[PDB]
Image (cartoon, rainbow, N blue to C red; front, side, top):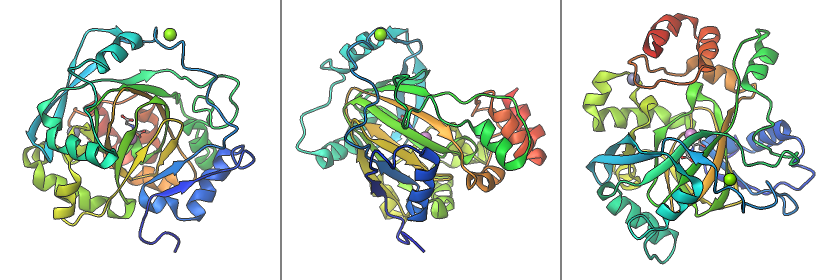
Length: 331
Ligand SMILES: O=C(O)CNC(=O)C(=O)O
Ligand SMILES: [Mg+2]
Ligand code: NI
Ligand SMILES: [Zn+2]
């Protein structure tokens, strides 16, 4: 079995290997990359996402989210308070202000220590989940707006044509902006490109050990667990590496820098934080190997998780027994 310790693998495809996206994912899996739940892909030196980032300031962040924490430094939840709209240029200036900017630090490890010590005492503002793309239309390789759609994959594998679309999302971050522990909708893959700015640190639990994380989360967030049998779908809970290590939960960590891709694999729980002002683009995708994970994915039916239009068909076709209850939670 390849990669039996479930380490995060880093790949350096050549420009020739960068042509066929599906083929390269299957290659990474042949080497055991999926066992970690997360992989890094460094694009060939010849590749670029677009020519420059000089003209992005007028993008609108319609609903910036202030991420307010509750709990203790290593075990907390966050809620999202909606703020007034602002442009990317306005948000960049805010991120660089004395109130929100990255503190002085020695290296990524020092910054990680400072994040876990101090996150809860601040409320950073995240421009998340903005439909759109920063890939140039002429970028033919690993263009996250030109991927094969999940609806087409389901149709190719299973023969059933379904409604829905699959488009990318932009994320504008600042110091301490935080992504809570989650797997993707329907335990899909994700791919994330860091277009510009400061790094993003990731934590990930191997898919084979995801239920260990779920059991700890039920212990640590006991009211939330009584409220919903899949409350991590709410995307609000954080648990630090120190707490994971104290409770014996297998995990790994890595820092993504500008110009690098990350892939999350089906049922790979992940969480993380931004180091400073940045912009990332991410989208969900599927492969043949995902289908079995989609069929087994947990679902929130309490009403909290509320997701896209396109998830309806996935539930309806892959999980017909759950459909009625889940749809009630959507309505
Ligand atoms: O970058 C972020 O805030 C969160 N991204 C992801 O969870 C992802 O790409 O799957
Ligand atoms: Mg602009
Ligand atoms: Ni994710
Ligand atoms: Zn729920």
